Amino acid sequence: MLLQEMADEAGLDLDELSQRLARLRDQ
Amino acid sequence: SNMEKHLFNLKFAAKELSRSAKKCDKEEKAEKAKIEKAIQKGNMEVARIHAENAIRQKNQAVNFLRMSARVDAVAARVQTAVTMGKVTKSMAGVVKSMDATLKTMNLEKISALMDKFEHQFETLDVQTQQMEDTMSSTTTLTTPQNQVDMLLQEMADEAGLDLDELSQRLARLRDQ
């Protein structure tokens, strides 16, 4: 987040995941 | 830089050749006068040497003038080059500056910032309206509506241009 913010400033472009993995584990 | 001083030297040599041609011209005049004042005394050789000297002065003068014109043209060309080079350097500088600025202050950042400006001042309008409502509610006894209306009507009739029972009836309705 810090890098993205400071890139937007300097002007140049560059949890649910684990939950879904848990879903798969339960499956 | 070096080109500038070299240009200065070129123009110096140009005007030097010019003044040298003028010097040769005035020397030609002087020799022509000396031959006049010498031929009167019956000197043929002295006149001859004076004459050839004058012709040499004239020829060298025209040559110096031609050379001066050439060098002036060359120096003018070099001046053009120097000025164009300064312009090019300045344009490169502003190009670098604009590149840095645009990379820093891009179009997207501009748009976002301007939208933020707009929304901020809309919020400020809301604030002003809130304060308007409150200030109009507070200072209401000292600024009735009927009084100001009567004043406006009277002063309009003067300047010449056209523009309790209610609550009692509402009370009647409330009682009904």
Image (cartoon, coloured by chain):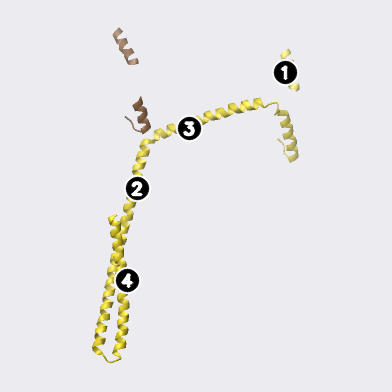
Q: Distance from label 3 to label 1 (Cα)?
A: 47 Å
- Which residue, given by chain and number where applicable, does mark 4 sit on? B19
Residue B170 circle label: 1
Q: Nearer the viewer, residue B21 or B84?
A: B21
Is B108 above or below relative to A26?
Answer: below
- Which residue, given by chain and number where applicable, does mark 3 sit on? B117
Specify the amino acid type for callout 1.
Answer: Leu
* Dot 3 or dot 1, earlier in sequence: 3
Of all residues shown, which one is farthest toward the top?
A26
**Which quarter of the rendered picture does the C terminus of chain B lie within?**
top right
Q: Nearer the viewer, residue B37 or A21?
A: B37
Please identify, in this view, whether the residue under mark 1 or under mark 4 is nearer the observer. Answer: 4
Specify the amino acid type for callout 3.
Answer: Phe
Q: Mark 4 belongs to which subunit?
A: B
Circles 3 and 2 on the same chain: yes
Residue at 31% x, 76% y: name it: B25
- Which residue, given by chain and number where applicable, does mark 2 sit on? B91
* Dot 1 or dot 2, earlier in sequence: 2
Quadrant in the rendering for residue A26? top left
